[PDB]
Amino acid sequence: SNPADHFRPNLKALTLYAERQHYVDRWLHVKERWLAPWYLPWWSPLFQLGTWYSQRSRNLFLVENHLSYRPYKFRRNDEDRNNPY
Amino acid sequence: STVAISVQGLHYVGTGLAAIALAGVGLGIGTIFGNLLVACARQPNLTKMLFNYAILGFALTEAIGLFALMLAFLMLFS
Amino acid sequence: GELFVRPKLEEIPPADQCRGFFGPLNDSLKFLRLLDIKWMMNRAVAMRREYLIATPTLFTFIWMFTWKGAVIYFWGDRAPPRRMDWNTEETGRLPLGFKPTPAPL
Amino acid sequence: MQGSWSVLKKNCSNFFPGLLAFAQQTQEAYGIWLRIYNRQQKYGPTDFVEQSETFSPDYHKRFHSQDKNMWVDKELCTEVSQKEVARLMTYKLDMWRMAHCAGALLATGGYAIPFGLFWLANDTWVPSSFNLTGEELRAWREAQDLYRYRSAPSYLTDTKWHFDFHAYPWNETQERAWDDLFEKNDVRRDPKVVRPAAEMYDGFIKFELIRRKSLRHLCRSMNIPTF
Amino acid sequence: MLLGGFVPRRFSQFNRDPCWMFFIFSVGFWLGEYPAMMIKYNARDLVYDPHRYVWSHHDDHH
Amino acid sequence: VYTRWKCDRLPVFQLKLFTQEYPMHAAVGIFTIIFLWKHMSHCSEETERKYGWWAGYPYWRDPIARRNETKYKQMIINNDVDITHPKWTGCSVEQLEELSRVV
Amino acid sequence: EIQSRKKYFQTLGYLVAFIYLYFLMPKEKSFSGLSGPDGHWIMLPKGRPELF
Amino acid sequence: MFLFFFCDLFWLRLLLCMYYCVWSRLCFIVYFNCLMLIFDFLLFCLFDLYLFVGLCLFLLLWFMLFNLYSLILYYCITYLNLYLLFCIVFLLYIAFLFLFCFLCDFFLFNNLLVGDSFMDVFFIRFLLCFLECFSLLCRCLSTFLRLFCNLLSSHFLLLMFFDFFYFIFVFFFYGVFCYWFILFIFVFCFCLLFYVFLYLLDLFAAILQLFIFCNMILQLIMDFLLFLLFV
Amino acid sequence: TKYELKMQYFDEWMIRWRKFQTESDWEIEKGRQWWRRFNMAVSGALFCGLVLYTSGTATLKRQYGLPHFFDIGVDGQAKETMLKTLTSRWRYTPQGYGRVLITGVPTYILFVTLEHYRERRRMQQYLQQNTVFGEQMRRLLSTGKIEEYLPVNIKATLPASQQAIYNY
Amino acid sequence: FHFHDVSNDAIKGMPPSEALHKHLENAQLAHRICLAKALKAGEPPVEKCALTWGEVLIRYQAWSEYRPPFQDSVAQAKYKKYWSKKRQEEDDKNPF
Amino acid sequence: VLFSTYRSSRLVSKEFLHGPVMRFRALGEYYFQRAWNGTLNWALPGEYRLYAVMIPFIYFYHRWHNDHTLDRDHVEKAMIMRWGGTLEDVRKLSAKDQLRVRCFTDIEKLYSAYGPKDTYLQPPGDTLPGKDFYR
Ligand SMILES: CCCCCCCCCCCCCCCCCC(=O)OC[C@H](COP(=O)([O-])OCC(O)COP(=O)([O-])OC[C@@H](COC(=O)CCCCCCCCCCCCCCCCC)OC(=O)CCCCCCCCCCCCCCCCC)OC(=O)CCCCCCCCCCCCCCCCC
Ligand SMILES: CCCCCCCCCCCCCCCCCC(=O)OC[C@H](COP(=O)([O-])OCC(O)COP(=O)([O-])OC[C@@H](COC(=O)CCCCCCCCCCCCCCCCC)OC(=O)CCCCCCCCCCCCCCCCC)OC(=O)CCCCCCCCCCCCCCCCC
Ligand SMILES: CCCCCCCCCCCCCCCCCC(=O)OC[C@H](COP(=O)([O-])OCC(O)COP(=O)([O-])OC[C@@H](COC(=O)CCCCCCCCCCCCCCCCC)OC(=O)CCCCCCCCCCCCCCCCC)OC(=O)CCCCCCCCCCCCCCCCC
Ligand SMILES: CCCCCCCCCCCCCCCCCC(=O)OC[C@H](COP(=O)([O-])OCC(O)COP(=O)([O-])OC[C@@H](COC(=O)CCCCCCCCCCCCCCCCC)OC(=O)CCCCCCCCCCCCCCCCC)OC(=O)CCCCCCCCCCCCCCCCC
Ligand SMILES: CCCCCCCCCCCCCCCCCC(=O)OC[C@H](COP(=O)([O-])OCC(O)COP(=O)([O-])OC[C@@H](COC(=O)CCCCCCCCCCCCCCCCC)OC(=O)CCCCCCCCCCCCCCCCC)OC(=O)CCCCCCCCCCCCCCCCC
Ligand SMILES: CCCCCCCCCCCCCCCCCC(=O)OC[C@H](COP(=O)([O-])OCC[N+](C)(C)C)OC(=O)CCCCCCCCCCCCCCCCC
Ligand SMILES: CCCCCCCCCCCCCCCCCC(=O)OC[C@H](COP(=O)([O-])OCC[N+](C)(C)C)OC(=O)CCCCCCCCCCCCCCCCC
């Protein structure tokens, strides 16, 4: 135990936390702001690169019909194997 | 009945078993050098070259022991 | 290892000489060549087109080692439980007396 | 050459006249190319017309073969004059650079405008039609020559180093040819002395086996856009 | 690569080069910190913490 | 004579190095970075308590609770959230007042 | 000349960084709470009542 | 979660800036074989077979600045994590593999089908091809595992032995003044011998492990190289 | 019109509030998936056709000539038929950048156009829905902002065993 | 008022939807109790009821994300394929 | 046109900070630019004195950091847990008492796996406080 503790980074300075929802929403707002202007047509490769893959992935998530339960990604406690909630 | 039992000392046993792996590794290394001598007395002009290969062999063979040793530590420190 | 030279048209043995799982699929059995995987493998080896056997394998491994492995691990569907929580199909519908907003026009 | 404000003003002033001239040159060059292409398809060898495949011996990758995929039309003077061929070559260079710029515009929509400002500030990648006077044309040619100077030595060094590191000439005459091929321009090279290097290198790397990095250096030296 | 440089023949020569002067100072620190620990941690008046059984790292990591 | 390493400035050489010398390696690295930040950028509170602190989690002050309290206070104050709304409490305001008078 | 000046400035900057890191910078998440930050949340929404 | 931390190389970066503002020749390289792939003259390769030299040199420098200096007490190997090493090896190995695959030459994989036409294709050759395709990925995994395990085991052993030496030196040196002084002197001499032996072993093993780390990558590259003969 | 910028917020919200996904919305998404696959298939077919048409004559002769892998007889007949059909008339056979453009630009345009108009179709479908998702879509297009916790505000239907929270 | 039992033993034989809803209800009950105490004391609610509100928020996020699978042809086929009679008998036999 | 891509576009004069730069280069070059200073992959020099100087310095600053920043956390945790479970409780002690406690922690560190186990295992019948003393 004590010997194992010697293999840690020794210059940790600061830790910041952010919810996935929050920064995903902020990123989407940035993307909408930069892809909104008229001088970037929807058929341009840049616009499709920005939008199509995200749309496809979100559609795949929505279509999902799984017989098992996937525990919430951001639970308070994910260390207990016998408690998915 | 249904009991969730947690024994603590078992992590020693497993650890010891992992060390048995070294019994091969060690032996294997010896074999290499054994042949090395029989190869240096059979063509000494290549000694240096042979030595290099032996070292390569040692480094590959030793690697395996480390794997086992890692497991021991994992179980010995958990 | 060494350079590979494709065989000439005259150096390629005839299809009738190839063997399947049990035996050659000669006349009256030619259409079974499509279904016999071993016959196709032997034919590919005979024609020096061994890549048809090797390329799909390696790529598949890569595809598993790179992209599908993690997808199955993180997003795959585990085995269903014994007592299953089916959907009653009651959720989502708007309540009685609700006045939905008009659609764009 | 580096970008400058004077060149930016020059190219912004002559932007639309340059585009109109480029369009006229495009029509003329299409006519010339149509004549040449019809003649090639009609009187060309079977391998040249059918685009015979030549694969490398190591990785079996197709590339143009100098013997089979290139054909000199000895009787082209009847249909097309020398000046027309020169016009077509110049237009091909201008059209390549314009095509790359247009592709960037279509790809990035309106976000290419600042990059267009960087583009018009330098004569390296603008068409020759943007110059409406002798002095402007001279400066444009100076920019092209500067790019050639920048790119050529890398190509020459790549070729020479790879050969010298992995092979040597067979005989003394080949040795002299190879050594004299890569002399600086301040001395005059005798073509008769240097010619055997062509066969010596044909033994090493034909045009069909040219590597991608060497090709990039060559296209840089030829003022051909590479991105 | 250990190719060359000043190499003192004996202890008395460590003072013939500033770098080896710093080295011998550091060696003095290294070797002299052990006697200090012997004196400090084997002292007569050193007393174990009365509350040493209140908490230990062993129960924490377990 | 012109060389990329000697004549170009550092950002330009960086772009050239990772675009015309090692483009595949850069692509794979970016792929791996995206994967790491998509699947290995989360830590639960229990995980932090078990492993997130050098000497161990100081339960005697519970800094995680204070951090969350600051977070939620900031969100409520900035977003003008009415935490007494029935959806948060599961009961009407009048029932809440009745409960307050009871307890 | 250029590299000498650049490396001189880089050396000074690295020296300052080294001193701060190994002699002034506190380690985060201290047990006692006397030194270093315990972490905090960022990118929280602001002025979005409809979000809740 | 975003953790802000720093590597343990800042002093070494300072020394690099101080000592390499001026040019110096390099004549000793841990993995020299990346520079000499071809040994028979008149053989040449159209593939960019020297592309690995720069990455090899930088990787050697980085791993040496970390691993070799880690023998100094309290020096930290900042990157010592299993999955981080997996990421590094994944980058290098998969990048070169994708370089060979993007070539779109399927004949390059003909050698994967092991054996000759005499061997049964489905029951022998195809199973050997399966095993070889598996072995490529296993080589990647073994490379990164071998690099991680060596460092971890060596440093665990060093820490434990140092702890034992501190214990006996501090709490049993008084025996020098006692009648059992000979036992303590024997033990102390044994500990000094063990100290020197461990340090020498670690110094050799670090360099050798870097050599093998680069050798695995170069072996991946060499397995798919084809050489033409000048005529 | 750029529907993706509007629809990304809606899709993220639906994922966050997927509990209230009726079977109708699920069918809508499945139809979107099916149409995406169909668009991929047709675009790939167009790309293959353009590649085949622009292929060199020698390339076609090698590809659709002897030997025959199976040698059944139908294989040879089909290969000869295709080879004759392609080599009968004159074909523009560009190389390099030109073949890239000819083969790719039509494919990209077709795929992008089909996908964009299917996105518009999905937006209309969700507009016509009589579920909470449809109401959210209408509110999004009206006010321009996604109203989270809408299902619990307007008291969207819940299973009989989970209506206690609405009991106020 | 009464808190639901969401212990591991109770949770083991429960559907995911029921467990999530019970957790949400427990969070709401705790939040309303804390708010009632704050109102009785007269102090502001935000200065006392922030953590309980956050717990309600996180339970809402976990509760709204889960959509029980629809019972259709493919889902029923998968369930019947995995849960054969042999597997059901084996599950019954196992005491764990 | 805005920024040059060439390193030749100078931003300062050739003589800017010439003196300090020359002193810095003199410091760098005196010991390193020598025939016997042949490095192994730029990391291990041939000059002995570089080792003799840099190994002690690296150890010294690493040890200072470890003693004053890293191990201090464990020491403070032991003090807090064994003497009240709160910082104020520890501060209620005098500096001498804290010194005694910290030195006992050092003792435990030096024993580690080889010292007596009665430093943390309470023998039966011992009269000293147990784990439930403050609970
Ligand atoms: C609106 C939607 C947009 C979609 C998104 C697009 C995104 C941008 C990508 C680029 C798009 C093209 C940009 C315009 C290029 C200009 C036109 C052109 O081809 O120039 C000829 C020229 C030909 O080059 P080459 O090397 O000589 O060709 C060798 C051939 O053997 C040459 O053959 P040859 O030797 O026999 O000689 C023939 C020559 C003989 O002719 C002549 O000599 C006369 C001159 C003719 C050409 C003139 C070009 C002028 C260019 C400048 C235009 C003015 C710009 C003004 C700018 C300022 C404006 C204010 O004539 C030709 O050049 C013909 C070439 C073949 C035609 C290519 C066009 C095909 C696409 C168009 C049809 C699409 C239909 C859609 C249907 C939809 C169905 C569903 O093109 C180029 O220089 C190549 C483009 C360079 C940039 C490449 C960038 C990467 C491309 C990747 C594309 C991948 C697929 C798409 C998806 C991308 C996703 C990532
Ligand atoms: C109206 C006009 C007419 C209509 C339009 C017509 C069409 C126009 C478009 C087409 C034009 C084409 C021709 C263009 C030629 C010029 C190109 C060029 O740039 O030349 C260099 C050009 C100068 O050219 P030059 O002086 O003429 O020299 C040319 C020589 O021949 C030297 O030549 P060279 O060959 O040596 O130079 C080449 C160099 C060109 O590059 C450069 O020179 C670099 C330029 C940037 C340098 C920046 C340095 C300064 C950095 C400052 C940082 C910030 C400082 C602090 C600021 C504080 C502010 C408060 O290297 C490259 O070519 C590298 C290419 C790399 C390609 C990267 C591809 C990535 C692909 C990704 C992977 C994908 C894989 C597939 C995945 C598939 C997955 C499915 O550079 C500049 O002028 C530098 C400008 C710097 C601007 C300020 C710094 C950035 C400001 C950013 C503001 C952001 C605001 C928003 C922020 C929002 C935050 C939320
Ligand atoms: C809220 C609290 C504040 C924090 C906010 C943070 C916001 C975060 C947003 C969200 C981000 C999420 C993702 C995070 C992922 C992190 C991953 C990570 O850490 O990986 C480990 C990894 C460790 O890398 P490494 O191996 O240690 O090497 C990186 C080192 O920087 C060394 O590498 P290198 O040496 O190769 O680097 C090149 C180096 C080459 O060498 C040098 O240039 C030497 C200097 C080195 C400086 C950098 C090292 C820093 C050392 C520690 C700090 C130094 C002391 C600071 C004192 C602070 C006092 C409070 O050159 C530079 O560093 C260029 C900058 C030079 C600046 C010089 C300034 C001179 C000013 C002179 C003024 C004079 C005024 C006179 C007025 C007179 C009036 C009369 O970190 C990174 O790779 C970088 C991560 C950065 C991610 C982006 C973060 C966003 C930007 C935040 C900027 C905040 C600015 C505001 C702060 C204000 C004070 C509170
Ligand atoms: C050149 C490169 C070389 C170097 C390689 C270097 C790398 C190593 C190689 C290995 C790869 C390493 C991995 C690196 C990471 C790359 C990314 C990655 O892995 O992403 C996977 C990732 C996996 O998806 P995911 O994110 O995990 O999500 C899973 C969901 O399934 C996603 O759902 P979704 O909504 O996105 O839809 C996906 C859909 C994708 O598929 C579709 O959307 C529909 C089909 C698309 C067809 C595309 C065109 C094909 C050609 C059309 C026809 C041409 C000829 C026309 C003329 C004919 C004349 C007669 O797939 C499915 O869902 C499966 C549907 C299967 C239906 C089967 C129905 C039964 C009947 C048909 C089969 C049985 C027939 C028996 C016949 C028996 C006869 C006796 O993405 C995908 O695979 C899907 C999106 C991309 C689709 C691209 C479609 C084109 C593919 C290329 C085709 C042509 C080249 C291959 C042949 C070459 C021959 C020379
Ligand atoms: C923001 C936009 C994002 C875009 C995303 C899309 C990707 C990027 C787009 C394009 C980017 C620009 C650059 C592309 C590469 C340029 C390559 C190049 O320089 O070629 C020059 C070359 C010109 O030189 P050339 O001398 O005229 O001819 C070449 C020589 O023959 C050469 O002679 P050779 O001796 O080298 O001969 C060998 C040659 C022979 O080939 C050729 O050169 C012929 C042309 C290619 C034919 C490919 C079709 C083969 C047959 C497919 C059959 C599929 C059946 C499936 C049925 C399914 C039924 C259920 O190569 C091969 O043999 C390679 C065959 C391909 C093997 C593919 C293996 C894939 C393995 C898949 C692994 C697993 C994947 C994941 C799992 C998926 C499933 C779950 O160009 C071409 O030949 C054609 C270029 C076409 C460029 C791509 C056009 C892109 C259109 C995009 C449409 C979709 C957009 C989607 C957007 C989404 C929203 C944003
Ligand atoms: C190419 C091969 C190189 C081989 C070099 C061999 C060096 C031989 C060193 C001999 C002994 C040196 C003793 C130093 C004592 C310092 C003071 C001290 O107290 O230290 C005690 C420390 C630790 O001793 P300790 O463990 O007894 O400390 C006790 C402290 N308590 C009780 C608190 C725990 O000594 C060391 O750690 C020295 C180990 C050196 C191992 C060799 C490292 C080589 C790799 C780094 C090379 C750096 C070169 C840089 C050059 C510039 C690069 C650009
Ligand atoms: C305590 C637990 C310990 C567990 C330890 C487990 C091991 C962890 C090891 C971590 C370190 C090593 C990581 C090595 C790298 C692994 C890579 C990997 O598997 O990542 C896969 C993952 C898969 O991504 P994904 O997980 O988002 O997959 C999406 C699939 N659905 C939507 C169905 C859920 O890749 C990524 O994360 C990167 C994705 C973005 C970059 C690629 C985009 C292009 C995709 C092309 C195909 C599809 C689009 C169509 C074509 C293009 C059109 C423009």
Image: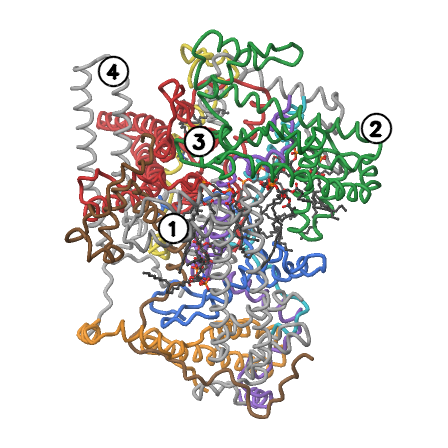
Chain A display color: blue
> Which amino acid type corresponds to the residue marked 3 in the rendered image?
Phe
Q: Which mark is residue H47?
A: 3
Q: Residue at x 27, y 33 (%)?
A: B60
Chain E display color: yellow
Q: Say few, some or many: other residues with alpha carbon within 10 Å of mark 4 (under 14 / 14 to 19 / 20 or more).
A: few
Q: Residue at x 17, y 28 (%)?
A: B31
Q: To which residue does mark 1 refer?
A: I80
Label 1 element class: helix
Label 3 element class: loop
Q: Chain of mark 4?
A: B
Q: To which residue does mark 4 refer?
A: B46
Tag 1 and tag 4 share a subunit: no
Q: Which residue is at the front of the view, E12 or I52?
A: I52
Q: Is residue B46 above or below residue H93?
A: above
Give the Cα separation between the discs numbered 4 and 2. Answer: 72 Å
Q: Which chain is red?
A: H
Give the Cα separation between the discs numbered 1 and 4. Answer: 63 Å
Quarter of the N terminus of chain K within the rendering: top right
Q: Given contact means CB atoms under 8 Å apart, are the residues at marks 1 and 4 in contact? A: no
In front of the other: label 3 or label 4? 3
Give the Cα separation between the discs numbered 2 and 3. Answer: 46 Å
In front of the other: label 1 or label 4? 1
Q: Which residue is at the front of the view, D118 or B36?
A: D118
Give the Cα separation between the discs numbered 3 and 1. Answer: 37 Å
Image x and y of residue D137, in percent: 79, 30
> Which amino acid type corresponds to the residue marked 1 in the rendered image?
Glu
> Which amino acid type corresponds to the residue marked 4 in the rendered image?
Leu
Image x and y of residue K62, in percent: 48, 35
Image x and y of residue F42, in percent: 48, 58
Q: To which residue does mark 2 refer?
A: D135
